Image (cartoon, rainbow, N blue to C red; front, side, top):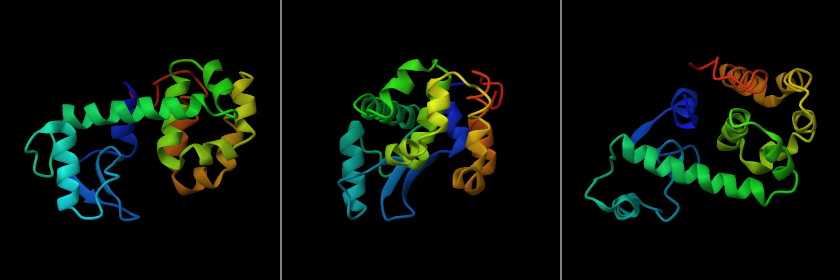
Length: 162
């Protein structure tokens, strides 16, 4: 199991350019193509990015290529974040993964608003908080997601997904 695989499961994979929910183009797992207001625009972004003919469709390892970079960038944003760095640092390598998963869905701004479970989280309270997480619009919006998420946060385990 890994964040990639955790995400394949979670939001899934798209290997051909799909314009999203809010116009963006996207490929792989949430990899935004920020420079395209087109699609032709989108393929260039893309070919260029990976550096091949691609033609609006990348392999599998390619999608992981991009994701990985997405993960790193995300890690960077958290670390410069005051509400978040402390918690994150305090997390294990499994829980951090879970915390990122949350980022990939709602984004920093989002995650950050959860001013409370994070406190518990920072404070090791593995169930109180996980209990705190079920009372969120998030829990209600995406249930099998949220479940699977506060269980990587309840147990330090890929038990869920695996």
